[PDB]
Image 1 (cartoon, rainbow over the protein chains, first blue to last red):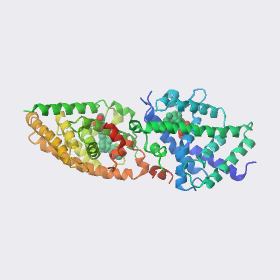
Image 2: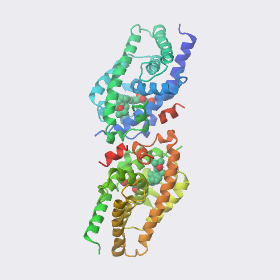
Image 3: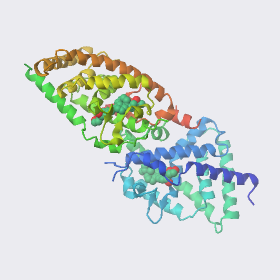
Length: 238
Length: 238
Length: 10
Length: 10
Ligand SMILES: C[C@H](CCCC(C)(C)O)[C@@H]1CCCC[C@H]2/C(=C/C=C3C[C@@H](O)C(=CCCO)[C@H](O)C3)CCC[C@@]21C
Ligand SMILES: C[C@H](CCCC(C)(C)O)[C@@H]1CCCC[C@H]2/C(=C/C=C3C[C@@H](O)C(=CCCO)[C@H](O)C3)CCC[C@@]21C
């Protein structure tokens, strides 16, 4: 049985996701329009910036992340944001389309659109495989949500200070994820290992993205298209 | 008579304007769409950033501004950019509409749209009067162009280093503007003083804008909507 | 510091 | 410095 606190942790983490995820994608109509050189970098940088904002609102509703010192909350978001975006993007991603489908065809980002935002296939190959490998895992929303809060609260991120407190949080979440898949996911004796594997998958997608981010940001004619928030979160600040 | 060099200075300054001014306003369809809180700050900040880019391309084609040290070229653009935008915006402005008309009604910025980008009527009152006072001056394109290069090359701008060289440029331009209105503008015995008055008008519109800019930029929830280039040019850097 | 991050986090 | 300004100015 799931305890009373671990069930509130589930209810509260799902609430957080439902507040910061818009299944209508209606706020997309206010990004810089896409183009299909880097015709897609402005609309896509807007999408990343939009996402970063939603990731911060998720994190602030995670139990006890609000309680962590502001330095810790920055360092966690600074190093985990791109993983949590890649993680949340699965919701729009479609196995059939092999593309994130965010409304109409104007927000159907296939693989070509992404190469036209400065990113090479060395990031795009592992990312599409991540998306379908996570998709095919047919996760319950209570596991997708939980996995996100777990990737966030990792102490093994550069420049965190109270390892023992954010580890105390993440473990408590890992406990909730494992008991959920046992008690609640019919067939998931293998699943919690599958999910924890996606976490290691992420960190390697993070490495490639943040390496290809340096390529774009060292070109001022490209960094010109980014947004104040992107430049702040993916910047190398301390 | 206009000399051979002063006529090339006119031909070259007009060329510069014709390269950096798009009378179709077609690149507007790629700004963040307008909304009519600050519903207009994203589209309008995009317009200002777009403009700053066109102002830099104008300046680089002004004779001998290219020759000035990069520090001087930065300091001139840093303090003159908003005046040269306000100056160039007259081209789209309409006495009849009392609004800049940049294509369809989607790019018809009346006075309400501008208050919805963070700016108060203390900037909007003097600016609309500037626009119609400059408009009614029915300037020749060779004077509108010349006045822009003159407002740029002012040595009395904060942090310029070679006053005597950029003064040498601006005078040479003032000489060309005066001889143009005498030899070429039928009725402009009063006009060169009218134009030089708009310059003093500008500096006072500059003061109000850059004061109201500090209000917006000290609010990170608003500065979030600006662009890397805006923040760089209107920033207080040295 | 991280102005916008500080702001968004309250 | 002014990265983007430097770039745009060549
Ligand atoms: C290449 C390109 C830009 C990189 C910009 C730079 C230069 C900073 O690296 C992105 C690649 C990897 C990040 C997420 C990618 C994608 C996310 C898709 C989502 C859809 C929806 O599911 C949602 C939110 C809607 C409601 O919240 C998610 O947050 C994001 C797919 C499209 C490509 C990008 C944006
Ligand atoms: C309030 C608001 C934003 C302030 C943004 C912040 C926060 C940085 O202060 C502007 C007020 C004063 C600047 C120019 C104003 C206007 C210019 C209009 C042009 C039209 C066209 O004539 C052209 C170019 C098209 C081809 O190059 C010009 O460059 C600009 C009118 C609309 C309002 C703004 C944009």
